[PDB]
Amino acid sequence: DLIHILLVEDSPTDVMITREAFDYYKLLNPLHVAGDGVAAMEFLRREGQHSDAPRPGLIILDLNLPKKSGREVLQELKADPDLMKIPVVVLTTSKSEEDVARTYGANCYITKPVDFTRFVEVVRRISDFWFGVVTLP
Amino acid sequence: DLIHILLVEDSPTDVMITREAFDYYKLLNPLHVAGDGVAAMEFLRREGQHSDAPRPGLIILDLNLPKKSGREVLQELKADPDLMKIPVVVLTTSKSEEDVARTYGANCYITKPVDFTRFVEVVRRISDFWFGVVTLP
């Protein structure tokens, strides 16, 4: 449970689905949320209010973002020699759109919302990620 | 992923379902299997062929066991001042039987087979167990 997860999603309903999924199914991975692209880059660069953010080990990225787009966030990520290494899953709004997105992006795409099932599929699609059951005090 | 899991189940079809679930969904927890009660106690006591077995952190126990029953295994477990501390989930064959089993055993019961969904519910029902996503080389 070392790696923190950064969810860049503007929909409060959809953020709620992921929060409750992590909660009800006992995911220990710290879930962090940015509601627009400008806040997402503030988190990654660890600037401003996020001056003490942890580096995420997984970024989950919607494309519909106010203030700064999903595309801008991804483009600024892959420019940075450090942020480029971080795994990115792009949220699509429809499995049909998901077929289109993989054709031209393939595993780094899942349809939203990210409930626990979809999050389990994310973990499956990403080679270096694994589930473990940990006992705790 | 420190804790090993001991599955005491005689059905090869049902053992197959759990093996593939752990495999396809990338559970790192070592899964160990005993096909009857006598082998299960051989594992716990770490005797004979299992002289170097690891202590399990979770035991999943069918009641239909040849050679030595599910009840015998549980009774010998709770006698032992060491083995008694280990979490035990009892497999029932029907959610109806599961309602009966909890009335008189409540969370330590799930209907078989143990696919990944049911295993996730086991983890939910057991206070000190948590899921974590771990990155790996």
Image: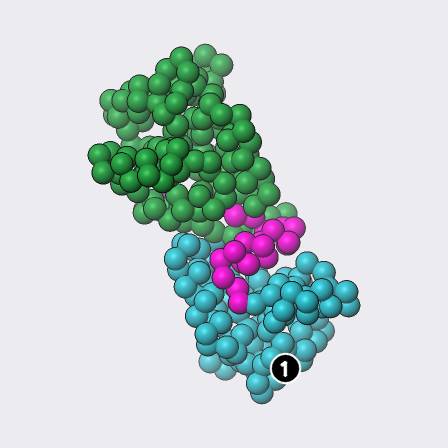
Chain colours: A green, B cyan
> What's the residue type where badge 1 is placed?
Ser
Please check the rendered image and state whether residue B120 is part of the magenta-colored stretch, yes or no: yes
Percent position of residue B66, x then y = 57, 85
Q: Nearer the viewer, residue B105 or B84?
A: B105
Figure check: B44 above or below B124: below
Magenta stretch contains residue B125? yes
Image coordinates for residue A1, horizontal then vertical, percent? 48, 42
The residue lying at 52 percent from left, 52 percent from top is A133
Residue shown at 60% from the left, 79% from the top: B64
Q: Residue at x 67, y 74 (%)?
A: B74
Chain ID at mark 1: B
* Residue B105 makes an appearance in the image: no
Front-most of residues A5 and B49: A5
- What x and y, as percent, mark residue A50? 47, 18
Magenta residues? B113-137
Local secondary structure at mark 1? loop
Q: Quadrant of residue A21?
A: top right
Looking at the image, which residue is at 64% across and 54% down? B126
